[PDB]
Image 1 (cartoon, helix red, strand yellow):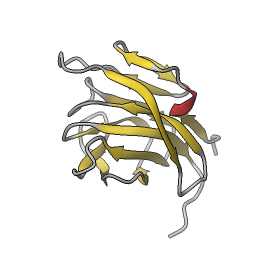
Image 2 (tube, rainbow, N blue to C red):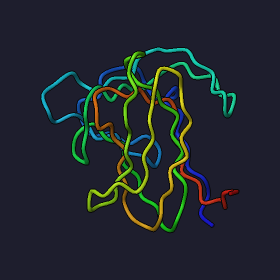
Image 3 (cartoon, rainbow, N blue to C red):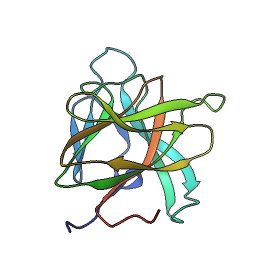
Image 4 (cartoon, helix red, strand yellow):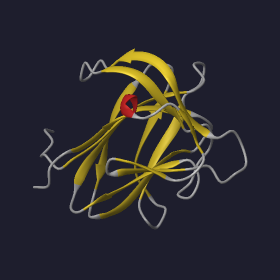
Length: 151
């Protein structure tokens, strides 16, 4: 019922992100752990899912939580969150979790060297946070859709 919300990281300005920042309907939760700041830099990829030509990536740059190196959004009813991302280390596979306000994982994905466009169930209205549970994940694209998903 509500319209799709999207954000292509390539539309962001390049640079470090030291304070919480809105990108469309999504919010980047800046690092509070004292380690290397989140930053947007140049990286060329073309999505195998949408064909979108990416030129930047958002380097979350560390293990996160709801208040550290996360991406937050709000859904008004059940939805699907789509994120295209990759491990920042091409040798590694790293978990990105989507959690509710209680910190419970409602969906997860594993991100490796190649980009993965992950569809993550948003089971009910509320606030949700995406973050890595192990080191750096680089994000290219974000989407929240309320359209019915095929099985």
